[PDB]
Amino acid sequence: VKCTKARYLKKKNMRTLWINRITAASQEHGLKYPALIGNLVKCQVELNRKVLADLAIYEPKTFKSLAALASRRRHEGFAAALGDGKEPEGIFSRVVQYH
Amino acid sequence: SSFSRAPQQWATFARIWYLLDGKMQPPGKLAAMASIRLQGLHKPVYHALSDCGDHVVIMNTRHIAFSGNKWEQKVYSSHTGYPGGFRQVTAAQLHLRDPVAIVKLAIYGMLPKNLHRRTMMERLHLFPDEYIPEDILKNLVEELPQPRKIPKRLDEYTQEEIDAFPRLWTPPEDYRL
Amino acid sequence: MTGKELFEMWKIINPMGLLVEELKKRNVSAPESRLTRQSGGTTALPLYFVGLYCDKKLIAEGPGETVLVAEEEAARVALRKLYGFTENRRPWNY
Amino acid sequence: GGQWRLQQGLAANPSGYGPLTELPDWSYADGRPAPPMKG
Amino acid sequence: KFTRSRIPEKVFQASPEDHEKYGGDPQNPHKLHIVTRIKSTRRRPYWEKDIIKMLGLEKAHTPQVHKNIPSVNAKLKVVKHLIRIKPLKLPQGLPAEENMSNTCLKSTGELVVQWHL
Amino acid sequence: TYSPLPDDYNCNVELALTSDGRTIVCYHPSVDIPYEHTKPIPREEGPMIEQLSKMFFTTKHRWYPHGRYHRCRKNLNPPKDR
Amino acid sequence: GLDVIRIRKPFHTDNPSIQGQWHPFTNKPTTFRGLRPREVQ
Amino acid sequence: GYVPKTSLSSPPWPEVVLPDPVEETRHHAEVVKKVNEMIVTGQYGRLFAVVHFASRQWKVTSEDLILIGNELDLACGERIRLEKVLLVGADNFTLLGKPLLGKDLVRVEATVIEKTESWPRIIMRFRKRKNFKKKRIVTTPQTVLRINSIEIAPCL
Amino acid sequence: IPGRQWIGKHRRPRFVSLRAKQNMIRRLEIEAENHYWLSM
Amino acid sequence: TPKESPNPPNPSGQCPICRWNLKHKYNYDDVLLLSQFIRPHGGMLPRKITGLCQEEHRKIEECVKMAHRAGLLPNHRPRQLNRYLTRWAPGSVKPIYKKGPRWNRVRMPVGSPLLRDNVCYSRTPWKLYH
RNA sequence: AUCCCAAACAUAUA
RNA sequence: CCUACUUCACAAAGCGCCUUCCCCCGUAAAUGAUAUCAUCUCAACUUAGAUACCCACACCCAAGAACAGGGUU
């Protein structure tokens, strides 16, 4: 019964491990984890957590690239919010659509 | 990169020393930073079963600054098994008795509550004042930032900002002061 | 030879000798070694990073638990980089 | 994050409708496509 | 005692402020509803369960379409606290038979024919 | 070298969009560690546990041996990863 | 022919890095002449 | 519109400002041209591709193996190509899609090496005092794919 | 505290967090939209 | 001696803090704002002479107190354990020997209650009682 | 009425 | 602990002897503010505020249930 009921915990706490690892790398590059994954999903880079953690380990400066991209998007978002009126959108903030 | 196998493993899992000033910092924030660093939750390689803890060295723990009135109010409780041994002591008293115990107990509370807590608390080093043994000082690598920004007082406010800050009211011609 | 690194297949000893031999065959000075990163110098689990240099430019670095093993493995690293047999090489094209 | 995805007119769940799930996931080497997914 | 609920009809006299708030169109009112369940049938009385079995809403977050007749409105008006109903706007007319197997639905509430994968 | 975030702690990475907008290209070269930032090479069964406890900084518990039951269950020929 | 017993990793990436595996000094700066903190000379 | 300097009148976060859009576009054009000449010449080495094949995301490189938890309707040793590549990277550059990358800028091949069924896994349900004791054996089917090559192409 | 601590005259009243209130408001706004789309 | 500068942005306000668009823009760390409302011996001036309002007078008084007990005006003594945001004077606060269970805890005050309407920048507000 | 009982933290863009 | 007294008499004992400590954080006194006088301070501000003990086979013993411990010059 434990061998059965443990598969759901397997998924649960492996996702927790990946979230912790990504938080470690993100803190290495100056960005908390909420900001990273949120503002990265706000650029249609639909990358899941397993690959992000595996990139934190086995590919450090492509992770640096993704973190820099996230910080860029965050700054563009804060600039847009600071826009008190009508403002052109940022350069990465643009949304690509598909039918 | 492109190292050999064993040197690559040693590079990955090697453990880095960390100094951490403590002057005019609240014990809890030092405790939080030390808690994350001791158990390895700053390495992307983290895992509980890997034991990737990294050493930590706090200094100036005598100049810890609790917030509010926590010196008078916060009380730490201990009890030897012998009757009447329920003793509990304020923070000021425990600071005078042994001025490395507030930060020690904070880091002890935050760490995970398992049979790895003792290893992590052994890899913590706490030194009350700026002194530090040389065989430790020549192991250090990094100096983590001070969490609380120490608000400087009038004494180090140079005249440029004293007179640049606008005078905001007009006392009458005559006054005692 | 897939996955097998170079020097697990080409069993040599005394790498820095072959390094200076190759760099002299290319008419360049014997490379000068320095200490890049150091963590835990006194304890029994140290990490020393030794970087070989070629007249103010760096051609490899390597980790070890002694400055000497670090020297040796940084030599192995540089020797790999020169011979175009690193781990980032283009995979064989089948 | 999926509230932002909705205020931009996307499926809140990237495994919903979008490029990621609609398009085929493989093709024979020469180029002739392959029978679609049962999903 | 607990009972059913009779909502006074004054709750359904939409104001002009409501009209300009949501995608209002009082005249030329919309034809269909797309309805999705967002709460559990359990911990809720039995007639709510029966209604949520009558309107096809078994699985949550699975959208189902219905008319805007006052009968179906009188059914929805007692499970309204378990459903999100959005108009099914049709910017281009409802599909023809040849291009019907190649249609799809967008989260904004629109049914669209131009869905090439 | 653009530094909204101070891309100097580690190295510098440059971000850009292809002309249309459906691909993002980032350029990250391996920044090399400078020379003038470098340094030159410099050219008995209870006390046993206590000394190993101070040298490796682990606590005393793990150093005592374990019984036969906890040493026939150990795997002699474990699988080799990679 | 391999035994049908459990499979631990869904992958066997024999060269699992292209960009340099992580050691604690990636992303950590360097200082003038290699001064560990609080030093003088 | 003036405030004397104070610890909380200003925002603690350091207010950055974005670059000018036209110069920003010129910079972006320059760097993409640089990466384009790098790809055209042959600077790169090995390549890693983050791929979305058939359930979920795999980080894949040449020569390696990937275990999929379902059948794929393909004879043994029958070459295949994996569309839906959402990251491809080398030593010096990496390209991310938004979300995906066109079928011309990245080409990921593959082959099927073996088709197996997983080890016999157990589903047992149990409840106390109710004589509820269910047992079942499940054998999921699996197929293992050898990734062969990842060819990037200059089309940017 | 007499027993069955969640009831009695000296019961312990639970606190209303901010995110619970935010969830209440989310459901309630959805209800307002339902009221509209059943109003025609 | 202190005077009035020729550029008060918002002249004729509710109080000389409102005459500088400050009413919710000072903490205890603002040493000079307090120093402009202090005698040479630590205790601050009557509100009549300065012209301050009731609430802002109270706020500057409390800020002066917390600034003293933090050790931020050492040249204002009337002639060691280091704190900040010391609400109550340390001579009249007792230890918390009996802190209740989860649901009736007694917690150590921090900050001052006259600074709730300050600007807030982290989304989780100031947590006065700790 | 055996022994207080989570360690902490007023502010980095929800 | 056994010198005497006392049951007893290589000793164990009491009804017989000798030793027993450490200022231990509690109080008020002044100057003085918002509230210019006035007021001990949920304002700042000067003061009445522990040791000691232990540490390197066999035969007897003031050490011992066995094992331990002191002695064998």
Image (cartoon, coloured by chain):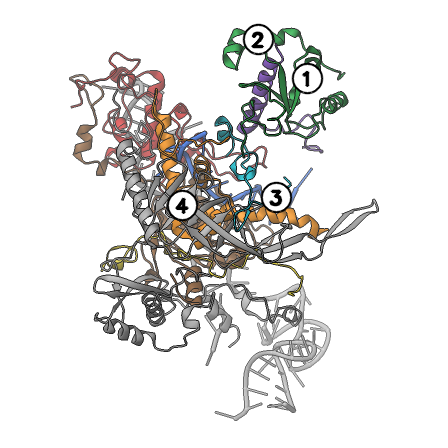
Chain colours: A orange, B brown, D cyan, E green, G yellow, I purple, J red, K blue
Say whether residue H98 is left or right of residue F16.
right
Residue with the mark numbered 1: E76
C-alpha separation, residue under disc 3 versus residue under disc 2 = 45 Å
Q: Name the subunit of mark 1.
A: E
**Kind of residue at badge 3:** Pro
Q: Nearer the viewer, mark 3 or mark 1?
A: 3
Q: Would residue B35 be seen by someone viewing this image from the given angle?
A: no
Residue with the mark numbered 4: H95
C-alpha separation, residue under disc 3 versus residue under disc 4 = 30 Å
Residue with the mark numbered 2: E28
Q: Name the subunit of mark 3.
A: D
Image height check: is F6 above or below H11? below
Q: Secondary structure at mark 2?
A: loop
Q: Crowding at label 3, few (<14), some or many (≥20) Cα neighbours within 10 Å?
A: few
Residue with the mark numbered 3: D35
Image height check: is B27 above or below C25? above
**Kind of residue at badge 2:** Asn
Q: Nearer the viewer, mark 1 or mark 2?
A: 2
Image height check: is I35 above or below B31? above
Say whether residue A98 is left or right of residue E39.
left
**Disc 1 or 2, which lies upstream in sequence?**
2
Q: Position of residue E71 (x, y in %)?
A: 71, 12
Are both tags, 3 and 4, on one chain?
no
Image height check: is B15 above or below A88? below
